[PDB]
Length: 217
Ligand SMILES: [Fe+3]
Ligand SMILES: [O-]
Image 1 (tube, rainbow, N blue to C red):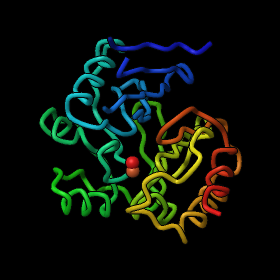
Image 2: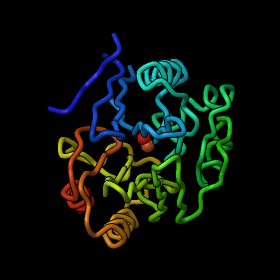
Image 3: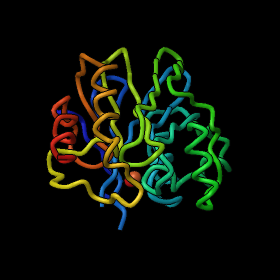
Image 4: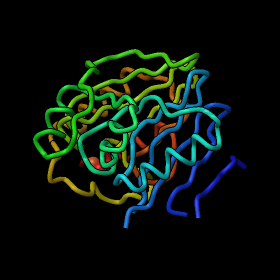
């Protein structure tokens, strides 16, 4: 049984392996990201719904792992992903994103992440390798996935629905005729996957990608 650690339960971290944890927060609706415990600091995939939760998440992981959060990867311009950007910027935490995500964050009144990520970007933090991939439009115009090639773990983000999701959710900003193609692009790039972390809900495997394809029918 994987180690699970909670705050007083609006924030929980669940261990996938020695250096990779899933962070999950409740907005007053749960949301997931990753905590990467690297030799050079903590790296998050996604912030949280707001600054209060983002501050608490950072404080929890810095205390536990005894290192600072240095970098966050923002996977699209929605509140569950980017809500804590003010906190990141004022703490000197680097907030990586594609240019489009940064363009949309600005449009919508949020402080801007770096806009440094391309269609494929390879990053390394200590020994931890991270690839970001923009597969095309889906849940939003800008959604990216994050791949950890040393573990074959995919962070699907909101592009990927959990087994418990029985519909597509908020499609206000979605591209329902391209989302399937974008999922296929992920499946084509990553042919051998070990875990898939959805934006919301339980961790799964490639079956979550197939589930999302079925929801798009
Ligand atoms: Fe979203
Ligand atoms: O979202």
